[PDB]
């Protein structure tokens, strides 16, 4: 029973939005500031140059035209709910890596009961400027450890510069368990990323190394 999966997922991502921005703030000098989801943004910190952590919620219908355009990748028209958190953080120092993270959930409705269909999607990665294999290895280890709490087959399947983990259209188990797997994946983030940024953010660099990495990576 518990609450509906939709309620529990929305609650989880909103709690993690708060837990993540606070964790990232703990190593910077600057704070994040706040359809249309709720987007928290950091800019011109001493550690983080630009970043955003967003939670979005959407209720609606998808046309048959829309669903038509869509079903390559999921196992008149349809009513749905979806929610998700998305983030991208870019450190000032080129020795510290960019990260992206996204966890989301989608379910169809229309005479409810419970279902028609639902899934989760997400994962997390790092995009380095300078590359440190040890940072990639810690990032992977802690996400592996999160996934191994559920089963050791998941990491080899979801894995994959540094990369990270990615899954989508994932509805293969009781959604209560998949909720816990998503929570545990979230909890892999701050211990890996704050560790990595701490150990890189004060490494010396010149303006030219930073400009060249910007050229190489874009933007």
Image (spheres, rainbow, N blue to C red):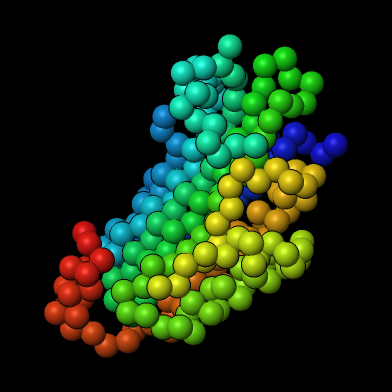
Can residue 22 be seen by looking at this rendering? no
Quadrant where the C terminus is found in the figure: bottom left
Residue shown at the point (74%, 68%) measured from the top left: 152
Residue shown at the point (71%, 25%) measured from the top left: 116
Name the residue nearer the viewer: 129 or 155.
155
Q: Is residue 165 left or right of residue 3?
A: left
Q: Position of residue 12 (x, y in %)?
A: 64, 47
Rendered view: 62 above or below 140: above
Can residue 4 be seen by looking at this rendering? yes
Quadrant where the N terminus is found in the figure: top right
Q: Position of residue 129 (x, y in %)?
A: 31, 74
Q: Position of residue 188 (x, y in %)?
A: 60, 67
Number of on-image labels: 0
Quadrant in the rendering for residue 203: bottom left
Residue shown at the point (72%, 50%) measured from the top left: 178
Quadrant in the rendering for residue 109: top right
């Amino acid at each position: 029973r518990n609450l509906p999966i939709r309620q529990q997922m929305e609650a989880l991502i909103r709690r993690k939005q708060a837990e993540i921005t606070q964790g990232l703030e703990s190593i910077d000098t600057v704070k994040f500031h706040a359809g249309g989801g709720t987007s928290m943004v950091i800019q011109d910190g001493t550690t983080f140059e630009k970043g955003g952590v967003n939670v979005s919620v959407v209720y609606g219908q998808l046309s048959p035209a829309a669903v038509s355009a869509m079903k390559a990748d999921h196992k008149d028209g349809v009513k749905f709910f979806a929610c998700g958190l998305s983030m991208v953080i870019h450190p000032v120092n080129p020795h510290a890596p960019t990260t992206h993270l996204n966890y989301r959930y989608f379910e169809t409705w229309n005479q409810d009961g419970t279902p028609q269909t639902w899934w989760f999607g997400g994962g997390a990665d790092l995009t380095p400027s300078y590359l440190y294999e040890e940072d990639g290895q810690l990032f992977h280890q802690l996400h592996k450890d999160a996934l191994d709490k559920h089963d050791t087959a998941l990491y080899p399947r979801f894995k994959k510069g540094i990369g990270g983990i990615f899954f989508d259209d994932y509805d293969e188990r009781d959604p209560q368990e998949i909720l816990k797997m998503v929570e545990d994946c979230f909890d892999a983030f701050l211990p890996s990323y704050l560790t990595i940024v701490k150990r890189r953010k004060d490494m010396p660099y010149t303006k030219e190394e930073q400009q060249w990495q910007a050229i190489r990576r874009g933007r």
